[PDB]
Image (cartoon, rainbow over the protein chains, first blue to last red):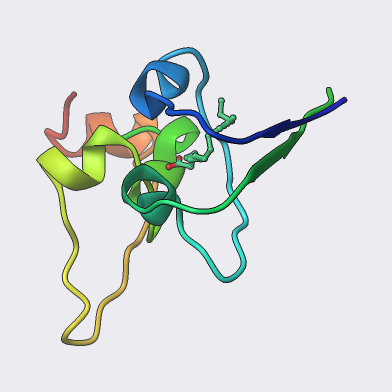
Amino acid sequence: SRRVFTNCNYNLTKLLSLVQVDEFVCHKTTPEALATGCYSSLTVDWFA
Amino acid sequence: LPFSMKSTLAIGSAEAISMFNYNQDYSNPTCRIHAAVTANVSTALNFTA
Ligand SMILES: CCCCC/C=C\C/C=C\CCCCCCCC(=O)O
């Protein structure tokens, strides 16, 4: 599944309270930037 | 710290570990070592948890 989010705000630490992270691989960003900075659009592709 | 949460000590992580408990400094050379003291070594020494 895929969702694209525009014109919204997100409380990220509430979403990280629901999961435990084993490993993250990031290119050209960091999760700290996604915890602080703003951007034009957000796309999430999630599967099991 | 257990191995199931060693990604919290990875660089760029947004977990509370880095921003409240241990913020590693990278201005000077470093090595972060995740090791396990086994039970037999733990009883051989006085190492407990
Ligand atoms: C439920 C998490 C995945 C869904 C996220 C959806 C929207 C949030 C968008 C950007 C924030 C991503 C930061 C995640 C930090 C995990 C890495 C870590 O610091 O350990």
